[PDB]
Length: 151
Length: 151
Ligand SMILES: [Cu+2]
Ligand SMILES: [Cu+2]
Ligand SMILES: [Zn+2]
Ligand SMILES: [Zn+2]
Image (tube, rainbow over all chains, first blue to last red; front, side, top):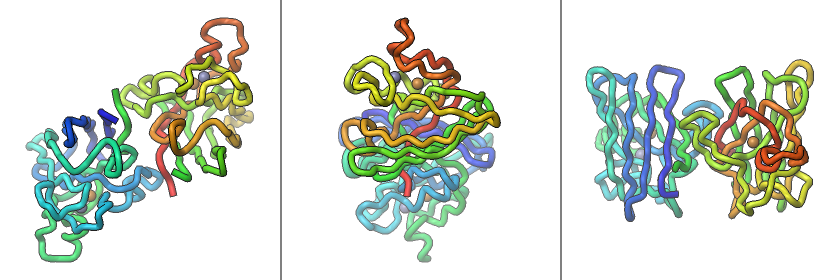
């Protein structure tokens, strides 16, 4: 696809709309999240677009290359690692990212997979424990939604 | 994919889970819908997996071949025409269909598109008006949900 959208909902107060657009070899992600705790939050594309068990059935981070977790700027990261989204003190996160590893077509396409906003900030694989290397210690998945094709 | 699932929800009482499985050149659709009015209901895959405006943004019936609307048995039908699903008097529709035109892979794949259950029965393009030929006079889309990959 050329454009996609994810509608995030959870069993909690967090919610939001994420838009994605193909611009060359990169993906531009925009949109907002409200209902969040002030500060930073991991934001990642989880591999399955399965909402049968809420956010739990979306599986792990999408990593077709079997790499360790990292930040959006690391060579060593999961295809779905988009770091953190920051909320202001009213709980609003303004997502603005341009990322060259995710894709709306081909092998690394994220269409049909899950976008998840996490309970805690992402450590970016730099925390010193096993759990940092697979999820960034981001804890709990607050809201998620299957990425689908859009206008 | 080999298996998919659609979770149907609306702003009304209707709800349900539809499962799909690839078996040869055909797709087997199973699952249930509750909260329905007794009788028949159109059931079709709408072309976009866009829930941004509820069920309204799913667009028209998926018809890659530009055909007129029909029944699941007609040569002349939309790829997404699966006819009717019948509720009993407690409002339960038991969906059981095996269909050879829809697909979980390739050109006619329905993964990422919308499954919609309608307010009225589908006339199957045999009603005698323009509207029968594009939607079966099924009226209002009661519930819908993006078709995603499953286990
Ligand atoms: Cu994550
Ligand atoms: Cu329809
Ligand atoms: Zn990761
Ligand atoms: Zn039709």
